Length: 582
Ligand SMILES: O=C1CCN(c2ccccn2)CC1
Ligand SMILES: [Zn+2]
Ligand SMILES: [Zn+2]
Image (cartoon, rainbow, N blue to C red; front, side, top):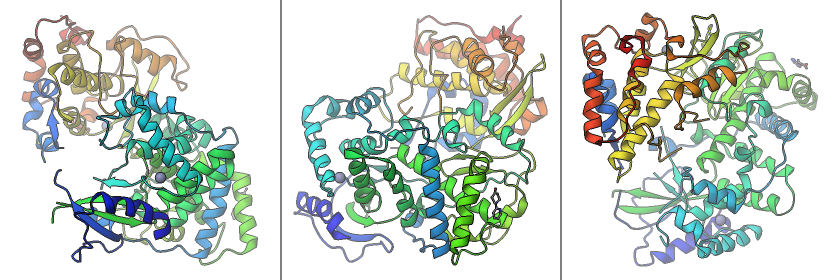
């Protein structure tokens, strides 16, 4: 308690000594409250005019238009302590899993240079604005690194002064750039050295790319076993127990020297003890603390969520296979039974899964898994949108399974070769491409963001008639040499000024390990679409009068946007499509 968090609390108390008051009408029940102080401030979603002017038919579709308009009673709930049997299963599995992930990898510190390079090419390091303007300026100033140095030596001494979260089914925990650096230095290796790649972790998909995920799910489907299960957890980050954070910290058992001490301090001082500041309109700032739940940088959050989800799903697989009888207590005989299962079949059981943070697909040995719920519920990983003891419903066809907000189609090229393509309802894709975040967008910056969406559609969603057409229109409307941009940056192969047919060939043919015949495609007309009825099922407007008028008159829409941008060099990409090819 206050020995570890008191120093951070003390320091904030004094900077607002004028305003400090133990408010008696504080809304917190599960968060430990400390005090309040005076503040006054808040970032809505803005429309991308380039994408909207080239998608006119969607101006009258509420599922698109409503996306641009506009639970903290889940952060303030509690999780119960797991039973002794559950605690044993988790400790044994976590010990085994860190060793497997560690066999071909070496834990190491990430560098100031690595951190600096990340800030100098816009990575979302969930930092706050103050003594320097942006992250880019702090990183160039030697005074910043001296503050970093002070905190760093405090961590080596087992104490913390400035690593405090700022809060804002979503929740982001911004920290000052310094606290973020010390997290990256100690635990960045998990992401930087690809500990959750599929090659290294067998279940993971880190670095895989949306063009690989369907092929990975089809490979899982080829295993003998039962249905494919894809159960979503209700509020995963809020269900991370103190036992989970202790099993995650066991990665430090694999470290040495300074690194070991710096990592032990991140886990002890910032993860297993948290200090948070939250805006309340009654506008004050509340200083609250708690020991459990996930509150880390988004990239460390992804790797540890993947770790703890792999652990939870192996234990659910053990329960289905009858490796243990009850979560109340494991016998030392069962303990040897659990380790032996892991040693003999653990790697095979990991390969039956695709796990992306809180998102999983599992093809178990048989359907006993569906009703194997005692460990999953007792670990706190309660399933969304199903009663606690109702058996999971599985998917009989890998093309139906949801994963990473997509489903996947098997698409046969005119030449016989097989593509496995990503897909989701087309209203979601169009509605997201019509939105920007933040202020001060020039017309050129807005155009270059529209071009990023268009080139993503050409590479990932070429099989959707409306998106191939709208992608060609946007790329025709934006100057040919203008570089696609994002402010917030899987593999993003569409982020390039290379010809999109050349990139398509590289991604789907040359580098595709599921494609034996490497014969290049010579034109976009060789690249297939879904069936027309399937395209409509997944939200196409093909068949509507509004869509036919848009497609027929597309050069008029392209010319409207070119006239706004002005006298620039443009390319016509529409004749890459059969219907505009004379
Ligand atoms: O190779 C192995 C997989 C099967 N396993 C067990 C152990 C107890 C109960 C069910 N299966 C033994 C080890
Ligand atoms: Zn600290
Ligand atoms: Zn689809």
